[PDB]
Length: 466
Ligand SMILES: [Mg+2]
Ligand SMILES: [Mg+2]
Ligand SMILES: [Mg+2]
Image (cartoon, rainbow, N blue to C red):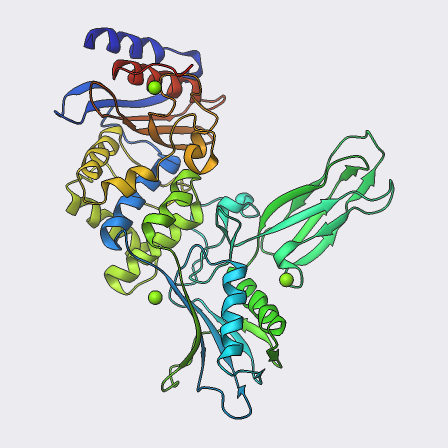
């Protein structure tokens, strides 16, 4: 039975899509420790978003499943008879799920505290983390796109998936020959608009492009949107997420009847403030709950903020250098052998990351016996599940196979890198597997990955739902 499995996986790995590729493929029975399959398990390879497995485990170790994140509003003293304050600070301590609505609610609280006039300036304080926005080896051509959002302790998260440091751009066709309409979303009045896009003839070709040119806070729209085309909506990153948070808060205060006389900018609560008066605050959901949108949808921003939050907890340092050492030490303390690990970020976006399939499987086993095992597993994509908050990045994979509803695994794909690692429950055992592919030059080998996970589900004793 074991020999059949090995031959079938051998055969799957002979696929032409893996031409020139190196593939770490390890399968283990977690009840015994029996190595069911091992090929190039000690080989160092880029994990892409499989890196988040390491990040999430360390976050749960260091911060705890019950950890929550805070945001506050502070003035030098409370408002008095006149209901006045001078300068005002919006202070973020790394909430990756802070919404525009959360800002309105804090603005309401400011007003309820007796503030009627902010006489001075409004500052956005993101000093809980450093101001290093992007990892060294991240590619600047990726910068406009949501997965490459700048990292800040104070950032507005968009939508139910909580994509941080972005605005939603909507482009709507007008009459043929007239410029297309561009709505910048939350960044209206913050980001600059360079709209060069025109409306094309009905039935013409859609060539619309939405950019943020490198080193600018300009949304540049070019090309042609057909008069009969549906509006085009895209998430685009902004420069300095905290300053957008400041702009949005300004508008919320005004909206809530608080007049702001001064300017909006970046700044930290002054050292010489004797006893800051906290006029409003907000507390995020607990980490266990945050893990779900983080891991199901592979949120890069969440991982990096969690890394800087680890640095804060272990060292009082909201930085990648401290956070990344914190991840390694946490993993060691969990029992994971971290010899093959090279940590350059938390998300896996960095091409400077290295793992081995043996290390991933090692982690999968150690996480399984950790007190937080259940919140950890609930965060992972479940193969072929149609509800996006359940299926995640596996929503449209392995449907109508034995893996559907059973395989829990994390994905990770970029140019020349693809990975799938997780668990296979069954009337036999809860198998743990890692598949890491590097070096292929066509599409990512997702079908090869699916084929292994399905064979494993079958080996485990499962059948396709019909
Ligand atoms: Mg706090
Ligand atoms: Mg606005
Ligand atoms: Mg099944």
